[PDB]
Image (cartoon, coloured by chain):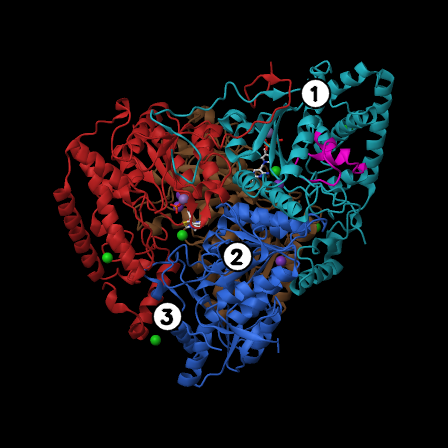
Chain colours: A red, B blue, C brown, D cyan
């Protein structure tokens, strides 16, 4: 019987390498089929009609906003945009399984979490336009959303940096005795970063109540997953870290919901991390599948579909137009919040700018900026 | 747009800066069978098109994608170079070079020294898009050269044009030291210029006096060279001031002699860069020029740099050390 | 040994620098129930004894070991701080801070700005052993402050003594901005001095004039303060020169006013640091003093720094900017 | 049937988290028991007597050198030292399975690989003393060994940095069509670093002929493995990356040899990475176990043991004494090899030093340094 502190195991008297099982990977959990029928009654969440309709409307409102802002970017009216197509179900389904005060970390595909949490169209637009209404004060590129009120940590561009941060936040929640989880969203590409290994391992050794939610859509920009990894996706990594793991069909809002709800329940109770890998497509769509479910229950119809399509387009267009005609913030906001306070040498730079603009102001877009 | 780009080696053709990079890389792979190019999304041609066509021409084993992991990209590249093979790594934006900082500063830069020259990674070059682009905000705009300038054992090189990019990149690739080559991304699709089709070299650690002048010395690198060229024109027309305009080109090791010789002549220096003032590379230049040219200085050396903030989105036109900021500082310096 | 350490708040006791760190940390955990300390090998007391006794006193949930992963340690600490809890991270040697460079520069430093102050990590402090130690060679000797000085949004703080360490570390821990506190490890077990048992604060961004003088201003930080104190004594005895000796204390944001006021008086400045000359923080100080005090300068500002090499093993006595190197530079400056 | 490019798998219609198997971990491969008897004849390597004696003598010579240099460090005669106690078998056993020209990357516990490859005692000592004979020119702390002739890449202090480098070297070897492997040694602590995740993943996606050799001795300085990870050691991580993996008894030179030999054979042939995790103790010792094997074959005895103990102590002491009385290198070597060439501004610093020493030289240890 081996006496090694690094591992718990028997001896073996023959040489055998352990092979990866990639062809027969971890199976993909699904609740409803492509015609929106529940496959296994024991797995029905029986979400109430008003919640399921909120899932549908959040996803479709997001999709409407994407169409309009994508076009705005193509026209150069905003400088950058990332859509949510194919990710509407992973985000709304998981968000619906969280408590409203669970803290979310993510990156570029997480706008649906904010939409489910009722973030105003006006503030999505304000961030993308960098206008005076933006609580981010116009400092980050578009789609770098954040909301303190809705417990959604401000997005940043460097991939995977949020992963070990999310773990730290979860550790703090544990200590505060919170009944709170942290969820951390990232793509399969981002999972290649060293910060992912850091986060996964810290979460396990430090026993943190966190859900790692990996979106696997088969690509990172131009890179297919065959050039990203060679094991059985990201779900197969979890067990090597001592993390309970599952794979789900990201086109199935109910599969996502069920996995997230159970992960949340166990994470908070056991102070242990869970890994959910949701398989999606790079864009048999989450909105269509849920629509078929709605029709099967008698919860929606063509008239409602048409009317909501029209109402959501009007709501997005009103927010869009308002956002475009607001001024940008005062240029003075370029200098605040670098530190909490403003150091004197920084104030000196601010004063330099004000003097410069007094003299050379006609060469700057002053009329577009507040005050 | 905040700048205007303007203006012996065999046949040339019109190339923009991305094309001139591709041409360098193509010449390199043609003549050096060990050479490979790798990084995120390089196989299909790169997000800025710098590697278009190269995989089809040279093979999938020589132009290939890595996993999304910058510390891995640099470590992997070091390892190629340890074997003597030419490793041309790409970091997708200079803003994302920081995960590799440990591999660059503690490993690449020190590899030769710490082994007594038993091992090296001299055949490594890291290329990355750099500098502001009008709307890149915090993570698509950065100019990190001053971070690297404090690390003995690496070279840091930044071109101002397509002709300069190809000759300097070839020199980095062939130089027997790990080099970081920062490509000003705002120039990738700006104006073309004639670029030799065949390989040629531009020397490292050599500044270029692009316009002679007798009243003031102006120093910059990258895109900011074009800003100071325009400043020189403004100062001539509006003030009757003759400006000597210098492109530093190599950040480290830098061409101290060329800069000091100019300032001994003019007696005035203005250095400009998009990077934040504090700890920026202008401080090293100013300090050194003050040490070598103290008796020749007629006025305090001016630094016109980005502010000491992160690089903002909507405020970019107010952040950058533009021609009006440079001009005004020059005006006050002349009137000192 | 290359230096000599020498020399209102209630009861004091004799403490060396490691003890004074432990006392700071102890006061912090006592008065702030959110505060936690974590890093590699901190639970048993740390490799330099800075956390001895703290886990037994405050609990395993507040003083704990992490996996061996510096990028994780900093990222984890940011995350604690995002929730408003005080996070005191340890990086085992400053030499090994580089894996966390991306988390420090792209994340911690920019957290408040980029969110419009919706989120912050102001309650994060990163402490790490720093500076030369006689035999530490490339990776147990480094002084990385100049790398961090080019990053708006962090503070960098370095003490010269046990009394200074405790008051400055308490100020970092309570400051509402992410701070890096570098502990000169050669001092950890050097001479003790009296240190208040109860908490007290020493202000950040304030230099300290430890000796008034009228002929020359000498600026340093960490251990090098003790070197320049000795230089001041040599210059008095051998040259009849009166030296004003200043401990910078905070690297960024730095106390420009205190340094400029001194140089306006003396008309001469010598800055010294163990870090390599090129891109070192002495360049920022020299540049700035030249800009503010140009008419008061009687001689070129001198920088006496480590050479532009990695930090060597057997050659350390020849590498460091010792009292004889500082003295000789001072001699030439006075004779200018 | 799922149509997701990120993974190959079936659907599952019930929610099931995948659990880690940590209590019943990957078993530990062993060839000989603690009395040095081969357990399973099919696993005997039948190494010839002269090779097995070279294994024994390399390990014991290392152990002798450790005793002497450890004491030297305690006395402050050298500034730093890392012993190899408990690691003698992992290093000699694996080195013996490599081709002499296979490139080795490692860190602090790899001196045995050099010893097996006949690195002179004089050069181990020269590095530790930083004397004129050191080809590293006295620039690194002690035990930072390297040898170009013996294909052993110079050690550096930052943990795990060698891992992705080793992978790059292996990629280059593949292209050169080498019949060469790279081996990369690291501890279980170092495996927590982001660079380990980088290396493991790159090696798999880029199909590199590399052996990852992880030494798991249950501790990283004061940190037990319960605070380092929560999966089944490091061997269990390999499959998640698509890496063929095995765990071996690090106190058994033959188990180590067999695993390394087979890993080498397959890595070079298949251009695929292998992971070996050798379980050792922090210091039923590799030297004793091999000694019992030798006695069982009639290959050693007490007289030989005594005589070799005496001869090895004399050889180490001769090298030690010689190393102490050599001068240190010329101080000019502080400036070379920073770049290949010496930049002019660096030459200027060198000249500054020479001028300084002309005047102030009596205050420096010039008599200890060459020229
Ligand atoms: C550290 C870093 N490197 C590279 C990039 C550029 N980048 C922006 S998105 C992306 C692909 C991300 O793929 P994945 O994580 O799979 O998410 P997806 O886009 O598929 O949703 C890359 C390389 C970045 N933002 N950060
Ligand atoms: C990046 C970095 N962080 C920390 C250290 C300090 N350090 C030197 S050895 C060690 C423990 C290493 O443990 P392991 O990898 O298990 O190897 P072992 O010492 O057990 O053989 C540490 C933390 C270092 N050298 N590098
Ligand atoms: Cl539209
Ligand atoms: Cl991006
Ligand atoms: Cl204009
Ligand atoms: Cl002894
Ligand atoms: Cl170490
Ligand atoms: Cl002396
Ligand atoms: K991020
Ligand atoms: K090179
Ligand atoms: K703080
Ligand atoms: K290493
Ligand atoms: Mn993806
Ligand atoms: Mn260990």
Question: Tag 3: Cα neighbours inside 10 Å, few (<14), some, or many (≥20)?
Answer: few
Q: Is residue A98 above or below residue D198?
A: above
x, y percentage for residue A249?
A: 34, 34
What span is in magenta?
A: D94-121
Tell me where residue D262 sits by quadrant.
top right
Lateral position of residue C173 relative to residue A301, left or right: right
Looking at the image, which is closer to me, B186 or B253?
B186
**Residue B57's disc number:** none
Examine the structure image and report whether residue D24 is included in the region drawn in magenta. no
Can residue C88 be seen here? The reply is yes
Residue at position x 81%, y 39% in the image? D122
The residue tagged 1 is: D43
x, y percentage for residue A355?
A: 32, 70
Judging from the image, mark 3 belongs to the subunit labelled: B
Lateral position of residue B130 relative to residue D185, left or right: left
Regarding ligand 6, which quadrant of the image does it lie in?
top right
The residue tagged 2 is: C281
The residue tagged 3 is: B1
Whether tag 3 and tag 1 are in contact, CB under 8 A, the answer is no
């Amino acid at each position: 019987k081996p006496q090694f502190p690094g591992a718990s195991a028997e001896f073996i008297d023959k040489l055998e390498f352990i092979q990866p099982n990639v062809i027969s990977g971890i199976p993909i959990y699904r609740v409803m089929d492509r015609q929106g029928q529940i496959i296994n009654p024991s797995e029905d969440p029986h979400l109430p009609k008003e919640k399921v309709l909120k899932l549908y409307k959040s996803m479709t409102l997001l999709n409407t906003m994407d169409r309009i802002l994508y076009e705005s970017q193509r026209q150069g009216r905003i400088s950058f945009y990332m859509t949510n197509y194919g990710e509407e179900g992973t985000h709304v389904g998981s968000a619906a399984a969280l408590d409203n005060t669970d803290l979310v970390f993510g990156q570029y595909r997480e706008a649906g979490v904010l939409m489910y949490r009722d973030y105003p169209l006006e503030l999505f637009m304000a961030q993308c336009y960098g206008n005076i209404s933006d609580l981010g004060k116009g400092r980050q590129m578009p789609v770098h959303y954040g909301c303190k009120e809705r417990h959604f940590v401000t997005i940043s561009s460097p991939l995977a940096t949020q992963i070990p941060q999310a773990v730290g936040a979860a550790y703090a929640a544990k200590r505060a005795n919170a009944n709170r989880v942290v969820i951390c969203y990232f793509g399969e590409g981002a999972a290649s970063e060293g910060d992912a290994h850091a986060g996964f391992n810290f979460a396990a050794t430090l026993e943190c109540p966190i859900i790692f939610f990996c979106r696997n859509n088969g690509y990172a920009i131009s890179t297919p997953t065959s050039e990203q990894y060679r094991g059985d996706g990201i779900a197969a990594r979890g067990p090597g870290y001592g993390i309970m793991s599952i794979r789900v069909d990201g086109n199935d809002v109910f599969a996502v919901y069920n996995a997230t709800k159970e992960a949340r329940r166990r994470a908070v109770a056991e102070n242990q991390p869970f890994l959910i890998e949701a398989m999606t497509y790079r864009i048999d769509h989450p909105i269509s599948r849920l629509r078929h479910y709605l029709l099967s229950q008698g919860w929606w119809d063509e008239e409602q579909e048409k009317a909501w399509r029209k109402q959501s387009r009007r709501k997005v267009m009103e927010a869009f137009e308002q956002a475009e005609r607001k001024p940008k913030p005062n240029p003075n906001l370029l200098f605040s919040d670098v530190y909490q306070e403003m150091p004197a040498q920084l104030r000196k730079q601010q004063e330099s700018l004000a003097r410069h603009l007094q003299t050379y102001g006609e060469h700057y877009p002053l009329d577009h900026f507040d005050k | 747009a905040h700048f205007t780009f303007q203006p012996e080696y065999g046949q040339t053709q019109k190339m923009n800066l991305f094309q001139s990079v591709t041409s360098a890389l193509d010449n390199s792979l043609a003549k050096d069978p060990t050479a490979v190019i790798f990084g995120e999304d390089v196989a299909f041609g790169g997000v800025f098109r710098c590697t278009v066509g190269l995989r089809d021409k040279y093979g999938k084993d020589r132009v290939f994608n890595t996993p999304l992991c910058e510390q891995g990209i640099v470590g992997f590249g070091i390892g190629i170079a340890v074997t003597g093979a030419t490793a041309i790594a790409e970091i997708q934006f200079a803003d994302y070079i920081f995960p590799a900082f440990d591999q660059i500063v503690n490993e690449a830069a020190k590899y030769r020294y710490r082994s007594g020259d038993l091992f090296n990674c001299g055949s490594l070059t890291i290329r990355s898009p750099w500098g502001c682009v009008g709307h890149g905000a915090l993570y698509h705009s950065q100019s990190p050269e001053a971070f690297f300038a404090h690390c003995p054992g690496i070279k840091v090189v930044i071109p101002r044009s397509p002709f300069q990019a190809k000759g300097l990149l070839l020199s980095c690739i062939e130089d027997k030291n790990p080099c970081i080559f920062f490509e000003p991304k705002i120039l990738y699709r700006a104006a073309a210029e004639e670029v030799p089709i065949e390989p040629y070299n531009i020397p490292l650690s050599q500044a270029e006096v692009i316009q002679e002048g007798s009243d003031v010395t102006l120093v910059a690198w990258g895109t900011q060279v074009h800003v100071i060229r325009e400043v020189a024109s403004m100062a001539k027309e509006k003030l009757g001031v003759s400006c000597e305009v210098i492109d530093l080109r190599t950040i480290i090791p830098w061409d101290v002699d060329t800069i000091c010789k100019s300032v001994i002549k003019t007696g005035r220096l203005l250095i400009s860069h998009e990077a934040p003032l504090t700890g920026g590379f202008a401080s090293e230049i100013s300090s050194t020029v003050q040490e070598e040219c103290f008796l020749n200085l007629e006025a305090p050396i001016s630094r016109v740099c980005g502010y000491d903030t992160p690089f903002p989105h909507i405020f970019e036109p107010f952040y950058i050390p533009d021609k009006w900021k440079c001009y005004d500082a020059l005006r006050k310096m002349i009137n000192y």
